[PDB]
Image: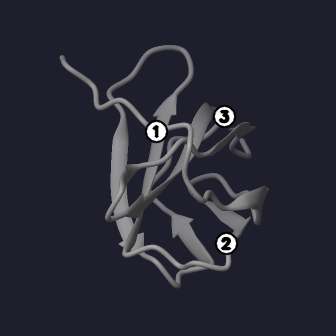
Amino acid sequence: PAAAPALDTLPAPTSLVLSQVTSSSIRLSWTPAPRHPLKYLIVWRASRGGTPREVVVEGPAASTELHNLASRTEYLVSVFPIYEGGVGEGLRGLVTTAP
């Protein structure tokens, strides 16, 4: 409905790496800013139309794995940093899971 705007001005992690792609999982990796957040918001959805899925992880996290993904499917994957100053603009990329 009313999605939450992201502040494009905030320390963000850098260099998103999407690896270990299986039929149902991908690994997400990023380079965190020197100031570690309280949390990170991670968002993934099927690129062709599907309800977005989310998980929030901690500030000093440098990795998390997404699971239970549908096979042969393209996902938009996003990483949102969560500090006290709001929600920051993050990293994103497309990955298609193995058959």
Side (left or right) of 15 relative to 68: right
Single out the mark in the foreground, 2 or 3. 2
Sooner in the amino-acid sequence: mark 1 or mark 2: 1
Task: Please report the residue visible at 67 percent of the width from the left and 71 percent of the height from the top.
Answer: 33
Sooner in the amino-acid sequence: mark 2 or mark 3: 2
Q: Amino acid at mark 1?
A: Leu
Single out the mark in the foreground, 3 or 1. 1
Residue under circle 2?
32
Task: Please report the residue visible at 50 percent of the width from the left and 48 percent of the height from the top.
Answer: 69
Give residue 37's mark: none
Q: Amino acid at mark 3?
A: Arg
Label 1 CA crowd tier, 10 Å (few <14, some 14–19, many 20+): few
Side (left or right) of 90 relative to 22: left
Residue 13: % across, % down? 66, 61
Residue under circle 1?
7
Side (left or right) of 69 relative to 33: left
Give residue 72's mark: 3
Residue 85: % across, % down? 35, 57
Viewer-closest of 8 and 70: 8
Q: Label 1, label 2: how many angstroms apart (C-alpha)?
A: 17 Å
